[PDB]
Image (tube, coloured by chain):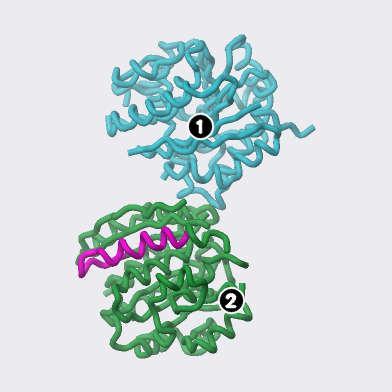
Chain colours: A cyan, B green
């Protein structure tokens, strides 16, 4: 019933992410929902650009671990790379589950590929990749993870993901089983553990979330997204949230940002009836 | 040849405008134009807010005057209040003409209203207003100010502007005389003096420049704006520029920032032929 919001304006225009989520009144609407909300502010941010990231992602994680116990954390960000720092840090050292809701698997290693770290955080978190990264950010067992909304993978990704054994719910599976059910399966699969959900904006259809780094046709519908957040929220097991890859520079009327603040409220309890 | 860019993320969500302007690739395009450019960064910012505004507009004023003689300053802003600081700083104790291109005349005193200070900058600069501000920002004689593109005026303002004797070219005059003639006319009214151009994105038709603080229908056309900049450019006396009131949160795929970076380039020498 207490909630902390910390921003990681990282872009190594997604760095404006944290600012749009705030202008979308994320905070005021959570209090409206009943929570007491403290804004911690922004974590300062000084292959391509590795150390800077691991550094800022370090500062992040330390901050989450400090945080009194029982406080729900909401990380507003740019790069999905922050996830490395957050998921680790919000775990508080516990064995937690990760519902990674992205259009991508964000699962490469430097071996599989671009060269950009933000396509590498889920893997590192599973312990696969450059050591300067895995050694300070490993925080979950591959078996403890579930991708949802995925509709675009690199060949090295398919392999690592298969070899590793990560439950992957691509948009084919969404179209096929419906989100209602996929939602249920995610909870069985990760039954018993606290859940840290990471929401990548590129998961909703571009037709709806235009402001994003890498649009990818045929994504979750507006309604669809809320169902997932609601079903999930119901479990009462959700403990932390990642709201990322929100690019105002590409958005319209700042609506991609509004969509997340809305899905955040669905995940933290808000119900129609 | 030397050009300095400085940001003022001040919203007292126009505080996001400076990133918007930078991401619209302002520096780079200026370099392509042939200028060696430096990013001084952002001036820290944190009735309503007189002291916090005065403090930042003072850090800005002071920072601009300390610039080496010859370096051309461009102030990237949110609020139009930053101009009390930059038109004073950018002038360096010299008599300069001010070409104010906003849909408003930002010429109110507390007596005539809204309450907000960002509708008073040109008044303060012209010496009318709170003493706490005029006392450090008054930097222009009303007879040396020219408003272009105006189409919104509070009663007190119209009166203050008449008493003051400020040359006003509202959209009605624009429609009657054309930008070319109004430009010959601005240049002549301010003949001999160095010129500082302040640009409120709201002066561009909302249809074209959606992301601005207060849209006011019936504004300049992308061609008229450019023409204007181009004529003021040929004069050889522009010496400083404010690019203000750009709000990405209300914009669309960042075309407002792109629309101004384009006008800056026009004021700074760029041409078709």
Q: Residue at x 35, y 75 (%)?
A: B196
Left/right of residue B128 with respect to residue A259 in the rendered view: left
Residue A63, placed above or below residue B249: above
Binning the other alpha carbons within 10 Å of mark 1 as few (below 14), some (14 to 19) or many (20 upward) gives many
Main SS, magenta region, reads: helix
Residue at numbered disc 1: A75
Please give the chain letter of the residue carrying mark 1.
A
Residue B257 screen position, x and y as percent: 43, 59
Residues in magenta?
B53-73
Q: Quadrant of the N terminus of chain B?
A: bottom left
The disc label shown at residue B152, or none: 2
Please give the chain letter of the residue carrying mark 2.
B
Q: How many marks?
A: 2
**Mark-to-mark CA distance, 1 and 2:** 41 Å
Residue B158 screen position, x and y as percent: 58, 83
Q: Residue at x 56, y 39 (%)?
A: A205
Question: Could you tell me which secondary element the residue under label 2 belongs to?
Answer: loop
Residue B225 in which image quadrant:
bottom left
Q: Nearer the viewer, residue B49 or B108?
A: B49
Residue B12, placed above or below residue A8: below
Q: Residue at x 47, y 86 (%)?
A: B166
Residue B115 screen position, x and y as percent: 60, 66
Left/right of residue A39 with respect to residue A31 in the rendered view: left
**Disc 1 and disc 2 in contact, CB within 8 angstroms:** no
Residue B83, placed above or below residue B98: above
The answer to whether any part of residue B165 appears in the image is yes
């Amino acid at each position: 019933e207490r909630v902390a919001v910390v921003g990681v304006p990282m872009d190594l225009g997604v760095d404006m992410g944290p600012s749009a989520l705030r202008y979308a009144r994320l905070l005021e609407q959570l209090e409206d929902l009943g929570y007491t909300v403290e804004d911690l502010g922004d974590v300062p941010v000084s292959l391509a650009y590795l150390e800077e990231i691991r550094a800022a992602a370090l500062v992040l994680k330390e901050r989450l671990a400090a945080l009194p116990e029982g406080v729900f954390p909401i990380v507003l960000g740019g790069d999905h790379s922050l996830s490395m720092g957050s998921v680790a840090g919000a775990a508080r050292g516990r064995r937690v589950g990760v519902v990674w809701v992205d259009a991508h698997a964000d699962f490469n290693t430097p071996e599989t590929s671009s060269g950009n770290v933000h396509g590498m955080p889920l893997a590192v978190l599973s312990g696969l990749g450059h050591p300067r990264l895995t050694e300070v950010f490993r925080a979950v067992d591959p078996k403890d993870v579930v991708l949802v909304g995925v509709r675009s993978l690199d060949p090295g990704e398919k392999r690592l993901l298969k070899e590793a054994g990560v439950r992957v719910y691509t948009m084919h599976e969404v179209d096929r089983l419906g989100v209602a059910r996929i939602a249920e399966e995610v909870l069985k699969h990760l039954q018993g553990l606290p859940l840290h959900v990471s929401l990548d904006a590129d998961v909703l259809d571009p037709t709806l979330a235009p402001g994003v780094g890498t649009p990818v046709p045929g994504g979750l519908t507006y309604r669809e997204a809320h169902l997932l957040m609601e079903i999930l929220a119901e479990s009462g097991r959700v403990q932390s949230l990642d709201l990322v890859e929100v690019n105002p520079i590409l958005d319209e009327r700042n609506r991609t940002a509004e969509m997340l603040v809305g899905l955040a409220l669905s995940l933290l309890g808000k119900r129609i009836f």
